[PDB]
Length: 81
Length: 81
Ligand code: NI
Ligand code: NI
Image 1: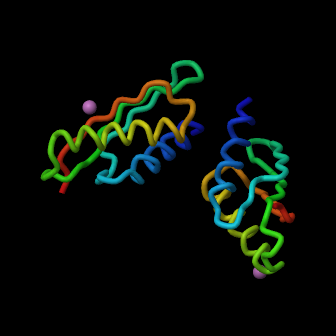
Image 2: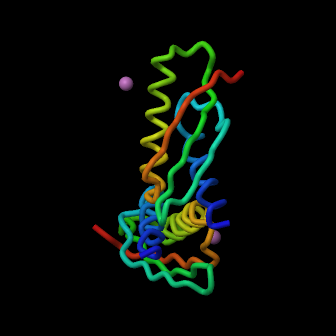
């Protein structure tokens, strides 16, 4: 439930990035005191693959800048209406 | 040093509020799993007392909204150049 607080922070930080149409999936786990996390964001189907990659990379920087314990974060994108 | 992370978050959140001219002082302590904290912000000497009170109250809401473990936060203001 310290983990719930962290997950909340991840979702919230991802959701503030331009182009994010929700957090579709988030798995977070501790590896010692560090967090490793895997997430899928929604994106406009009409974005280019390159734009979706940009948004992912912006999510990664936004989330890692906010949540200093994260030491690995993978972000993928899926079309969401 | 989990406390350092929390203090950092408090300062950072206070500093993003309009009218804050730094965090002059921050004392934070755990009361169980909750944080109680006392802070002093800088404010423009030419602000009114009422504006300084507004900024304090905005700091309180900004910090408490960001840092869910805080259950008591006092914010005061001092002139800062
Ligand atoms: Ni690239
Ligand atoms: Ni008032």
